Every structure is written in C-alpha cells, then in structure tokens.
Length: 222
View: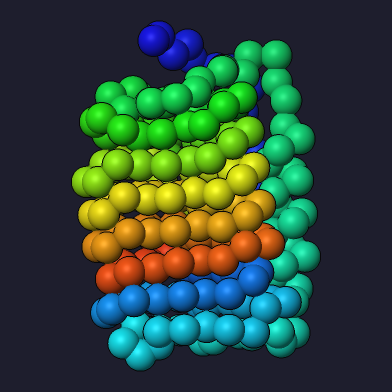
C-alpha cells in the first residue's frame, strides 16, 4: 500500500459553535468510571447524560440550550462539508491503515476504516498548517492500544474523520483529531482523545477515558 503525495491543499473544516466542545452527542451520553473531559460537553436533542459522577467534566455541560442547539447545526454543516469534498488527486484508502503514514490532503474510504495492527501516522512534512480530511463510508474502529501519531509538525487541530455510521475505539487507544459521526461514537476503557468526538444523531459512550482538545485548538497555522 503506497500513498502518493497530494498537491491540492485542503482548507480547514469550519466547526462553528462546536469548536470549544470536546464531546457532543445527539441521543444520549453514557459514561462508566473516572472519565475526565477537559472541554465542553453537549447533548441535543436528547436529554440523558449518565455517569457524571464518577465521570468528571472540567468544562461546561450544554443540554438542549442555545449553544448545544447551534453546535448540532454546525456539526451537520461540518459533516456535510467534509463529506462533499472532492479533488482530482484525492487518495482512496480502506480497511486497516495501521503502519501507514498519511501526508496532507483528502482521503476516501468506501468501506470500513480501521487501525487494527500498528499505528497510523499523520505527517505534515514540515508544514504545521497542513490539513488532513478522511471520508469514511462505513465505520471507523481501532483495536486495543492503537495510536494516531503526529510527525513532521502535524497538528490534531488539523485532522478530521468524517464517519458515515459509527466509530468504536478499543481499550487504551490514543486517538487524535475531530471525529464527526452520523450515528454513535464509543470509547472503551482507558482510551484517550486529543481532538473531539462529535456524534450527530446517536450516542457517545465512554468508559474511563481522557478527552482533551487539540493543542492550541483555536489555531490551524501553528
């Protein structure tokens, strides 16, 4: 599996009022154990968030309020933007991408995308402003202990995963980037995210996780 180097420069995907959220769900949120979120937590139009405590939110909880409701509209916009992007030099990838390095640009998976063996590296080739957009027609999953790694100055603020169904991250996965799923997102015990978990219509399920926003999350150039 050989990944070519794209020339088309992807623009950032505007997240609007979702930018200061670490986690957003649509139908419900369920947590088990000592999860910690540093960032805001949103739910709309659903009402039920379970498991805080023992989960801890270092941030503001927004349920069916002005900010959460706008954030749902804005994640729909972002999802549709991500899904509609096309470029003559975009790259098709699918299945297990463990062991691969992805350079900047646009990627499309017509089936499920996974990190099943080894780690996936995003390599910005010395340009921190680089953007990486991955379109996924099905699910996004990881086995236990998988990692999203950054090289060449790549930034978690600049990586986007558009997921047309649901995502599931195995125990102790260290994931990065903004995950925008149509349906649900699940993190198993001890998994972590530097990024955002933004579920449009389904649920976010957590167990003993650590969530933080991207380093310098309000910037894409550095």
